[PDB]
Amino acid sequence: LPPLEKTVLDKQQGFNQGEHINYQLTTQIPANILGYQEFRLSDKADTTLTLLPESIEVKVAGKTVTTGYTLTTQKHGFTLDFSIKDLQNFANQTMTVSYQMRLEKTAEPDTAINNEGQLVTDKHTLTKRAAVRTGGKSFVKVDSENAKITLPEAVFIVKNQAGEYLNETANGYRWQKEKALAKKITSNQAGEFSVKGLKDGQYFLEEISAPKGYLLNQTEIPFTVEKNSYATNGQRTAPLHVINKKV
Ligand code: NA
Ligand code: NA
């Protein structure tokens, strides 16, 4: 029975919202492919993943293939419905399908985000899912003397190790040099705020606006994004306390 592999490239640190994720389906065309009535490769992903249809590339033994199939594409997946007769030329060879999907801003940190690769023939159906993640961190803005006095209207931007600034575009995040494009994050009535949709890393907060009555911390505030720095099975990780001294 023809096999099925699904892989994701460089998934070790998770991914940013907006990042283009490289996926691959691999199978092997059976020697007796002419015996089959049906042969279809597909992916159907979570709605947190958007397919880039122009990315899709079918190769056999390294060579790009453009006929011998009908491609269907939708927002969160595709189907390649192959002509049996045409696959005879590729009997006994490896076929890969490379494609990309964008992680949307609806992707929650510390959740399994699945795709589902599938090979359907008339004899059998093979299914293999893969999973990706993004990360985040919670914070709470507090008085330096009293951790229970939580402070609204504190405004921060985020920086990476290079001193670049997190920008929100329509589709997700990008690090860039212009401070005026920096996405702003503000502590709420409970003093709380978070950063969601970053891959693993060491990043920093820079306070650009203090709560009324309080000083601006001139020191950048380091924080780590990694697996479970935001949540563990729905239960939220405890916020980093960000302290403010009063005038
Ligand atoms: Na087919
Ligand atoms: Na959290």
Image (spheres, rainbow, N blue to C red):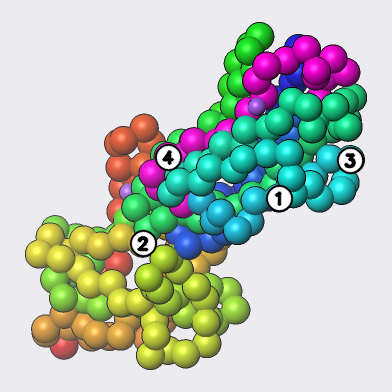
Image-based side of 80 in relation to 113, left or right: right
Q: Which residue is painted at 59% across and 27% down in the image?
A: 118
Residue receiving disc 3: 61
Q: Helix, strand, or loop for circle 2? A: strand
Q: Label 4: how many residues lie within 10 Å, few (<14), some (14-19) or many (20+)? A: some
Q: Mark 2 vs mark 3: which is more N-terminal?
A: 3
The answer to whether residue 153 is seen in the rendering is yes
Q: Tell me the distance, in whole angstroms, between the alpha carbons under discs 4 and 3.
A: 30 Å
Residue receiving disc 2: 195
Percent from the top left, x then y, of residue 208? Answer: 30, 85
Q: Label 3: how many residues lie within 10 Å, few (<14), some (14-19) or many (20+)? A: few
Which is closer to the viewer, label 4 or label 3? 3
Please state which amino acid type lies under the numbered disc 3.
Ala
Using the image as rendered, state which of residue 199 and residue 38 is in the foreground.
38
Residue receiving disc 4: 46
Q: Tell me the distance, in whole angstroms, between the alpha carbons under discs 2 and 3.
A: 43 Å
* The disc label shown at residue 57, or none: 1
Q: Which residue is painted at 12% across and 60% down in the image?
A: 190
Q: Is residue 4 above or below residue 10?
A: above
Q: Which residues are magenta?
A: 28-50
Using the image as rendered, state which of residue 19 and residue 196 is in the foreground.
19
Q: Residue 27: within the magenta?
A: no
Which is closer to the viewer, label 2 or label 1? 1
